[PDB]
Image: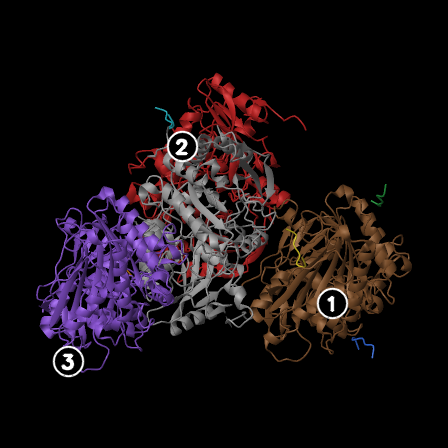
Chain colours: A blue, B green, C yellow, F cyan, H orange, I brown, K red, L purple
Amino acid sequence: XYXXXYX
Amino acid sequence: XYXXXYX
Amino acid sequence: XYXXXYX
Amino acid sequence: XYXXXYX
Amino acid sequence: XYXXXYX
Amino acid sequence: XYXXXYX
Amino acid sequence: XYXXXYX
Amino acid sequence: XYXXXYX
Amino acid sequence: CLPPAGPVKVTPDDPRYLNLKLRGANSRFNGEPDYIHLVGSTQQVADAVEETVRTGKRVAVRSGGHCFEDFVDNPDVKVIIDMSLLTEIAYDPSMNAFLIEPGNTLSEVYEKLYLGWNVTIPGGVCGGVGVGGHICGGGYGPLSRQFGSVVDYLYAVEVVVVNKQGKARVIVATRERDDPHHDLWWAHTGGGGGNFGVVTKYWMRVPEDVGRNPERLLPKPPATLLTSTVTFDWAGMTEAAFSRLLRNHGEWYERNSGPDSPYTGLWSQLMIGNEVPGMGESGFMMPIQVDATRPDARRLLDAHIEAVIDGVPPAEVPEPIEQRWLASTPGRGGRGPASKTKAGYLRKRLTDRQIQAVYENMTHMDGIDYGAVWLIGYGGKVNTVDPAATALPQRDAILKVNYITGWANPGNEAKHLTWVRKLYADVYAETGGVPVPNDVSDGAYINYPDSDLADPGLNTSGVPWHDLYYKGNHPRLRKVKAAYDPRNHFHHALSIRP
Amino acid sequence: CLPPAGPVKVTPDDPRYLNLKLRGANSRFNGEPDYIHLVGSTQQVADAVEETVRTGKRVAVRSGGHCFEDFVDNPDVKVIIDMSLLTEIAYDPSMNAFLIEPGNTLSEVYEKLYLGWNVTIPGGVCGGVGVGGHICGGGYGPLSRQFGSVVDYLYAVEVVVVNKQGKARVIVATRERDDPHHDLWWAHTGGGGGNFGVVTKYWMRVPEDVGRNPERLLPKPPATLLTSTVTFDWAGMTEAAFSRLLRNHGEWYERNSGPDSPYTGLWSQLMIGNEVPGMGESGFMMPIQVDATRPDARRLLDAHIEAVIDGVPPAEVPEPIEQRWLASTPGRGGRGPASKTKAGYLRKRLTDRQIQAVYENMTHMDGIDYGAVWLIGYGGKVNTVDPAATALPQRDAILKVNYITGWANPGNEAKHLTWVRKLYADVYAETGGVPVPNDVSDGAYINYPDSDLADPGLNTSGVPWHDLYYKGNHPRLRKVKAAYDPRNHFHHALSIRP
Amino acid sequence: CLPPAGPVKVTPDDPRYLNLKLRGANSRFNGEPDYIHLVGSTQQVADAVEETVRTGKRVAVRSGGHCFEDFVDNPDVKVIIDMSLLTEIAYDPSMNAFLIEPGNTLSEVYEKLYLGWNVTIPGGVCGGVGVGGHICGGGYGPLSRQFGSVVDYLYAVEVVVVNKQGKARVIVATRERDDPHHDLWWAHTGGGGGNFGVVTKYWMRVPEDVGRNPERLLPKPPATLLTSTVTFDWAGMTEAAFSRLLRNHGEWYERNSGPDSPYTGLWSQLMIGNEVPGMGESGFMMPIQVDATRPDARRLLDAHIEAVIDGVPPAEVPEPIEQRWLASTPGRGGRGPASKTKAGYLRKRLTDRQIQAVYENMTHMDGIDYGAVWLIGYGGKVNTVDPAATALPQRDAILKVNYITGWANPGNEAKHLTWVRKLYADVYAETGGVPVPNDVSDGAYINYPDSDLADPGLNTSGVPWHDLYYKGNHPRLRKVKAAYDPRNHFHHALSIRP
Amino acid sequence: CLPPAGPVKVTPDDPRYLNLKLRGANSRFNGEPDYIHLVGSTQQVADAVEETVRTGKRVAVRSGGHCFEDFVDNPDVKVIIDMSLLTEIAYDPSMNAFLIEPGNTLSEVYEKLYLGWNVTIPGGVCGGVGVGGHICGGGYGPLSRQFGSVVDYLYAVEVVVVNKQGKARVIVATRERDDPHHDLWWAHTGGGGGNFGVVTKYWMRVPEDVGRNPERLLPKPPATLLTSTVTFDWAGMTEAAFSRLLRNHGEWYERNSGPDSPYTGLWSQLMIGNEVPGMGESGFMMPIQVDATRPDARRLLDAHIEAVIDGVPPAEVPEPIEQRWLASTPGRGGRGPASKTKAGYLRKRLTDRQIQAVYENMTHMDGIDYGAVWLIGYGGKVNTVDPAATALPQRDAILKVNYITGWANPGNEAKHLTWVRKLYADVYAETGGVPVPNDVSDGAYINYPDSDLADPGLNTSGVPWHDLYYKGNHPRLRKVKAAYDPRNHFHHALSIRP
C-alpha cells in the first residue's frame, strides 16, 4: 500500500 | 459607525 | 487588463 | 529621479 | 556680457 | 562683466 | 616548544 | 645564485 | 558546477535584514524574526531546519512572498528560511523532467521554459509569485482550461522533513505508483505550503510517455493570443443591467466549461471593482484571451463577448488585439498595499439572490479604497481529473470567485475587513457565511487562504475550514502530515493538523 | 550538475523568433536575421560562431539589447547569437573571483551579489542593461566615484575567437603578470562589444590581496544612501540664471572630483530636459545621492546642493530621504521608444560659449517630444588608474555629458535627429562639431556609441571616431584586433579595424 | 561606575618600591628612581607627566617591563610612570572598536578577547609582555602570517603629550584620513615606545566596514592548532649538514611567504641554540604550528617539515598534536636572567657565507651559558601593506633573525656581550656589521631595540640606527616628534630626535 | 604605351584654379570648391571619389561644363572632379564597340569618328558640350529624326559607384539582357548625370550583329547636307501673321515626324527671338538641314519651307547651300552670358491659346536683352523605341520647345527670370504652369534641367518634377539609385532619391 484510490 | 475588528 | 501590474 | 523607469 | 557670439 | 575672476 | 615560559 | 650543487 | 552560494544568517544588524523582512507582497503583515536564513542548496536547507529544531525557534519558509495570509510575516515566526538563492530551471535527464527550484518567480519560469524548449506550465498570471508556494498549493491561470492545474504536471518533489527524533532528512518523492513516498508527492499536488517540510525542488512533466524529448515534456504555449477587454460603466449599471450581466456570464460558463469544449482555449475574468485613479486593474471590466492558433479564435471570442453582454447597455467592446506569447515581460513583484481576499469555487452560476447581494454590497462601499468581486474562468481540462487523484478536490468547477478589498492607510483596516466580510457572508448567508460545498459552491482554494474560515463568529456553518479547502481529501492529508511532520514543526493558522 | 540548455536555432517560422528579433531596447533599429541562435554554453557559442564562419553569414551577439546603435539590429546581420540562457553568477574558487555570465542583467547581478555576499560592482543604473556589452565597454554608474569603473574589477575573460583558418577557439585571459593573453584581457577593459569575439564569461574581483573570503572580493555597497532631487522650473529660468546654474555645477565638479575628496561618496546628475506628462525621468532636475555610512553625509549633501543652486532662483529642494541599498528592484523592462544619444567627456566645465549653445538649443525645441542635456557625475576613484592601464583612456574627467532626444512617432525621426545634431555641433563648434580632446573635452565613451562621430559630414574636426573613443589606446587595440580576429568576422559601424 | 584607583607616588621607603623598581624582565638593567608613580586614569597620567616637566625630572613609562634595552631601568631615570593599574579591555561603542589599556599583558588580552567575543590580535607569544610598549612598537607573533602585525588593527590612540609651554594635554588620534591628529596615530603604528607621549588607551579593530558586531571587529583565532617540534642534535652534525639545513629552511621561507600562499596559516621558528639543562626553550629545535581549522593543515605541516629536513637527519619528528586555542595559560612573566638580543630582518635567506659565520660562532662558545640564533617565521599577510602606510617599513620580509645570549652571573656579562657581538658582526661583516637593507637584509625591528646599532665602533656601515629601524619612514616620524613633543620630554637611547 | 596624366588637386592657390572653376558655360552659376580634382584614369577617378567620401566633401563631376542648372557650380559643392584629361576615342576590340571618354567634347567625337572610320553619333549641335553629361542624359540633335538618340547606341558604361560601406567600386554595365548590372546600363540611357556615380567610359555601338568591322558599328553620317535659313521680319509680324506661322510649323511637324517619313532626313528649328546685334543666333529665324545624299533632298527642303511660310508675308528665303559633312569643324565657345532655359516636349502643335501666350510675351519684353522661344525638330527614328526600353519615356514627340532668356548684367537677373517664368506659366496655365503629359505636352527633357519644376510656387500642377522628366520610368530609376548609390553621395537639385 501507500497510494490511495478510490477504485 | 461600521468599523469592527477585533484587533 | 488581465496581466498583473501594479505600476 | 536617478533610478531608471519607463513605468 | 561673458557668452560669445557673433550674432 | 559675465566672466568671473578673481584678479 | 613555541610557548614562552620560563619554567 | 646561478651555480648548482647539491649541498 | 561551482559551489552554491550561502548559507547566510541575516540578523537584524545586517544590512540585508530589512529588505528580506519586508519582501512579502501584502503589507498588512509584519514580523520580526531573530534571523533570516538564506540557503543556496538542499544541504543548507537541511542544516537551517535542524538548527530551528534544536533551538526550538518557530520557522517559516519564504519563496515568492505572495501569501495571502500571515503565514510567514507574523510576530511569532522567529526564523525565516528564505529561498531566494534557489533558482535553477533545467531539463533533468535523470528524472526525464524539468527541475524548477522554489526561489524562482513564475515570470522567470515562463521565460526560461519558453526560450529553452518552447514549453510552459499552466500557472498563475502575476509574475512575482514564487514557485515554492504556488506549485504545492495547486497553481492555475489562464491556460488551465486548456492544460489543467500546474499540479497535473507535478512528477516529483524533493523535500526536507523532520522526523520524530528531530532530525532533518531529505526525501525525493515521485508519483510512480511503486515509490514508497508516493503519498508525500500526492500531498504536494494541492496540499499547500508550510505543512509538510521545505520543498527544495519540483520536477514537472506530462504524465504520458513521450520519450526523452524535452520539448514534448510540457505543454506548448499558444504562439499568439487574441485579447480584448470589455469595459463597463458604473453610471448606467442599474440593478437590472448588473444582474443580467452576471446571469449571462454565469450561464455562459455553465455551458462552456467542459473539457471537450472549443472554449477550453478561452479564458476571461469578470472584474467587478470600483475605479481607482492610480491602478489599471481596477474598475469594472472583463479581460478575455483566446488561443489564436485556432482558425476559429476570432469567432470564439466574439461569441463569448456577445453571450456576456446581451442586454447590458453600459458594455464597451474594443477591437481585439493579437499578441505574441510573452511579448511584454511578465510583471515584476514588490511590496503592495494592504489587502484581504476571500474566495470560493462555483460549479453553477451565482444564484439570483447571490447576484443581488454582490450588487447591494458593491453599491454600499462608502470609504472603501478598493473593493471587488472577480469571477475567474476555470474548469475545462482541469475537470478530467478525479477528485482523489491529486490533493485538489474541486474537479467540476467552472469559476473561482474572489472577494477583494485593499486599503492605503493602516488606520482604515477595520472598515475594509468589515466591508469584505459582510459581502462574503451575505453572498453565502444560506450556508453559514461560507461556500459550503453544495449544488452551486464547492468550497475554497488553499492558495487563496483565509483565516476567517476558521473563525466561528464568521463561519457558522459547522463545516470546518479544512473541509472547505480539501473536502474528502482531508483525511489522507492528515495521514501524510502525521507520517512526515510528526512533531508539527511546520505550521501556521490553516496548517493541516497532525 | 545538469547539462546546459540549448542550442536552439530560431528561424522565422519559430514562434520565439519575433520576441528575440525585437528585444533590443531602442526601437529605432530593426533587422531580419536568417536565424537567432540561443546558446547555453561556451561550446555551443564556439559551434554557433564556426557555423557563421563556414556559411559566411554576418553575425552579431546580443546580451542585454541596450546598444545605442544598430550594431545588432540592422538589415545586414544575418545571425544573432543571443546570450539569454547564459546567466550564472557565482563565486569561482579556481579563479578566486566572481564568475558573471553575459546574459545576466545588471539588476540580476546586483541582487544576487548583494544577497549572496553583500558585494556589488560599480556599474550602470538601468536594470535591463546586459553584462555582455556593459562590462567590456567600460560600465560605470553612481558608485564609480567611490569605486571606479566596472573594468577596474575585471580579473579575466573567456572569449570565443576565430583564427585565420576560420576555426573557433576559446581563450581564458587574465590580468596577471606573465599571462600569455594579457593583451586580450586588456582589450576587454573598455574596448567595447562586437570587436574581438564572443565573451562567454567575466570574472570580477578587487585587484588587492584580500584572501579568499568572497565577501571581500568585490566592493561592499553602502547600507544606506541619503538621496534628494532638486527640481528646477523652466518658466522662472532666465538666460542668466541658467548660465549661473551650469557654471555653479561645473565648477563644483572641477573642485570636488579628486580620488581623495570626501565627495567620492556623492553622485549627482543634472538633467536639463523638457517636461513630458507620464515620463518620471523627464524635466529639469538633479537627483543626488550620498553614501550615508559616515556622519558627514548630510553635510556633504547640503553643501553640494547649495553650491549648485547659489543665485539660481527657480530651484526647489525637498528634505533628503535615507534609502536602503536596493530597497526597490531596478525596474527594466525591454523595448522602448526611439531615441538618439550623443556624448562627450568633460575635464572642466562647459565654457561660457558652450553653455550659451546649450541654452539656445534647449529653448528652441518646437516639435521635439523629448530633448535633454544630462551632466553625469564622474571621476573620483576612476581617476586613480593610468590612461593606458585599461582600454578606457579618460582617467581625469569630472563629468560625462549626454545629448539626448527621443520621439514617439517614426515619421518625426528626421526632425529630432536634426535638433540633437545641431545641439551637439553648436556645443562643439570650435573643434569641428565633436568633443576633440583638449583642455575642456576628452572625447567619448564607447558604451554610448554614436555613428555620427564616423560621419565626415557631422564630424569635421579631422579627428577620426576611434581617436575620440580610445585616444592613445587605439594603436594597442588595433594590434589586439589583428591578433585575435584576423578575419574581421566581428564587426559593425564603429568596430576596431585590424 | 566606580572611581579609579590611584594615584600613588611610591618613594623608596614604601614597601611597594622594590617590587616596582625590579619588575623589568631583563635583570641586566637597573635604576633608582626618586619615585614610581602608579596611575589609574588618563587624568592621573596627565598630572604625573606635568609634574615631571615642572620638576625637570627625567621620566620613563613602564607598562609590561619587557624592554630589550635600558630605556626604563637606568641611572638617569628619576620618575617611572607605572601603568600597572590601567587594565581595561572592553568594546567601546563610541569608537566601534576594542579599547585595550596599556597595563594589560598579552596574556590578559588574548584571554579576555577570546572569552568575550572569540577574537584576538596577532601579537607576541611571551605572556608577560605589556600592551603599552608592544602595540606602538609594531608587535607580531605566530598569527602574523595569517593576520598581519598588531598595528594593522590599530584604529586610535589616546596619548598624553607635552606642548612647548610644558602643559600636559590629552589627544585622541585615529586612522581616519581627515583626523586632525592622523599623523600622531600613524607614528604609533611602529614608531616604538617612549617617543611621543604616554599612550593611555589603544583602540583596535579591522579596517573594513563590518558593522557594529564586536565579534567581527578583530580576527577570529583558529579554534585549534596542529603542532610539532622537530629536534636536531649537535653531536655528529657537520658544517655541510648545518649549512644544508639553513638553506633548506630559508629557501622554503622564500617560496612560501606570499600573502596568497596556503602557508599563511603556518608558522615556525628555527632555534639554533646550545642545550641548557633546566631550560625547555634552549637547544636546537624547530617548533611549528598550523591553523587546524583548514582541512589541508596536516599536509602543510608535513610538507614544511620535509623541506626543512631534506638530507639533514633530525633527532626526532614526533607525531603532530592538535591543541585548542589558549588550551594552557601563557606562563606568567617576572624577572629573568640577564640577556642581550641583536636583530635583523630577512627578505631572502642568509647567504652561504653568513650561514658559515653562524656555524663557526655557534661551535665556538666556550663559557657561554646560552647563545643562539633564532629564525622566526614572518611575512604572509604582513606583506599586503605599503611600507609607508604604517611606521613599520619592512613589508616584504620572510623572517626575523635574532642573535641571542644570556648569562647567569653578572661577572660574565663582558664575555657574553663579546660573543654575541662577534657573531652579529661576522654575519653582517660585508655591510659594516649591521643589517643594512639590501637584497638579503631589511634593517631591524624597533621592539627589539639594540643600542649597539648607534655605536660607531660596532656599526661601521655609515647607515645610522634610525635608518636601520625606520628606513624611509624616519622623516615623517621626526616631523610628528617635533610637532607633538617639541621639548623632547620623552627620550631614551634610541629615541626619535625632533 | 604611357602612363596616364594626373591626378592633380587644384587648390585656390594653384594657377589653374580659376580657369577650372570658371569653365561652366552659364555665367549665372558660381561656386568656390575647396579643390578641383583632375583625373586621368578610372583608378584616379575611384581614388578621387573615395577621398570625397572619407572627408565628407560634397562632390560634382564636370565633363563639358554645359549644365543648364547649378548642379556643378554652386556654393555647396566642395570638390569638382574634372574630366578634362579623359579624352580617348577608339575602337575597343574586346568590347566590339567604340570607347568614348567623358571629357571629350562632341566636336572632338564627330571629328575623330569621321576621320578614323566614317561614322558618327546623333548628338547635339553645340560643339563644346561634353560627352559626360550629354550621353547619359539622352543627347540628341539634327540627325536624331534619322538615327535616334545617342542613347540608342549606348552599349556599355564604366561607372565608379560608392557602396553602402563608402568604398568606390568600378562597374562595367552593358546592354546584354543577362548582364548582372544591366539595370545600371539602363539608367544611363537618359537617367541624367550626377545621379548614380561617375561615368569614366561610354562604349557606343549599333545593336545588330555586324561582325567585328568598326566601319558599320555606328551610323554613317551624310556625305553632304543641304541647308537654308528662313528669316522673319519683326516689323511685318502682325498677331495674324505670327499665329499662322506657328500653326503651319506645328501641323507640318504633326504630319511629318513618323519613322517611315522621307522627312526623317530633314531637321529644322524655329527660333522666335528678339534681334541682338552682335549675336548671330538671335532674331526670328528658322535654320533647316537635310541629307543631300537623297535624290529627293532638294524637294524635301522646298516642301518643308513652303508649308511653313504659306500665308506669312514677312518671310524671306535665301538660296540653299550644300555643305560637306564637318566642312568647318564645330566651335565653341567658352563661358557665356547668364541665361535661363525652361523646356517642354510637344506631341502636337501648341494650341491657339498657347500661341497667343507666346505672342503676348514676345511683344511685352521691355528691358529684356534676349528672350526667345525655340521649337526644335524631333521624333522620326527616335520614336521607334518603346518608352520603357531606355530611361527616356518620350518616344512619340514631334518637337522639343525651349523658352529662353539671357542677360548681359547680373543686376537684371530678377527681371529676366520673371519674364521667362511668366511666359512659360502663361503657355502652360491650364496645367499648373508646367508641361503636364497630355494630348499636347509630354513633360521635359533631363538634359535641359530646370529647378523651377520642383518649386511649389512655380509648379502648382501637383505633378512632381520627376514624373515630368521621367514619367513611367521613375520607379525603375529610383531602384537603380538605391542599388548603386545607397548613401546618396551623388546629388543636386533634380537628382533621383533612393
Name the residue that disc number 1 marks.
I188
Q: Which residue is mark 2?
A: K477
Residue K25 vertical position relative to residue L404 in the rendered view, above or below = above
Task: Work out whether disc 2 and disc 3 sit on a shared chain.
Answer: no
Q: Is residue L121 visible?
A: no
Q: Are marks 3 and 1 in contact (CB under 8 Å)?
A: no
Identify which amino acid the numbered label 2 is placed on. Leu
Give the image location of residue K142, x and y in percent.
Answer: 50, 48
Mark in front: 1 vs 2: 1
Residue L18 in percent (x, y) is at 16, 48
In front: label 3 or label 1: 3
How many numbered callouts? 3
Mark 3 to mark 1 CA distance (whole Å): 95 Å
Question: Please, what is the three-letter code of the amino acid marked with disc 1?
Answer: His
Secondary-structure class at tag 2: helix
Task: Give the SS element for disc 1.
Answer: loop
Residue behind mark 3: L213
The answer for which chain carries disc 2 is K
For mark 1, name the chain: I
Q: Quadrant of residue K109?
A: top right
Q: K287 or K87: nearer the eye?
A: K87
Badge 2 crowding class, 10 Å Cα cut-off, few under 14, some 14 to 19, many 20 or more, is many
Which quadrant of the structure image shows residue I143? Answer: bottom right
